[PDB]
Image 1 (cartoon, rainbow over the protein chains, first blue to last red):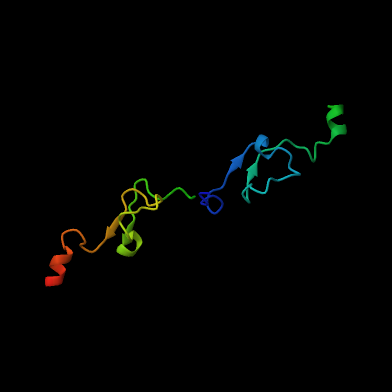
Image 2: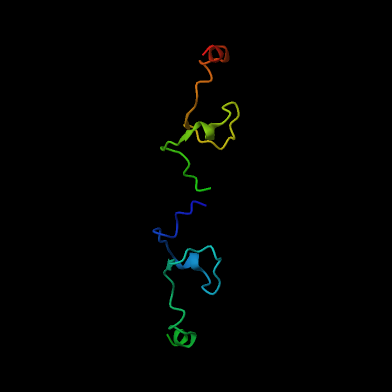
Length: 50
Length: 50
């Protein structure tokens, strides 16, 4: 509604805000930065051994 | 919707924007400045003589 959020107004969010990275509410600004746990490289078989 | 109508700003508009000063559309920010013709002191009897 302000609109001045997306040009020079970068946002950084934790993994809680991102939540499920598969689904995006379409209101998330492009270029959103999020800190998330390694769900891609750290596969389930690797964690069980650890 | 942006919300930045006026908080420490000032909006200057001509007499066209003000229009009829009796009615305000309730969206005009407080502190609006208009350059209106003298309808108060310059009464109609004075205008006819001039």
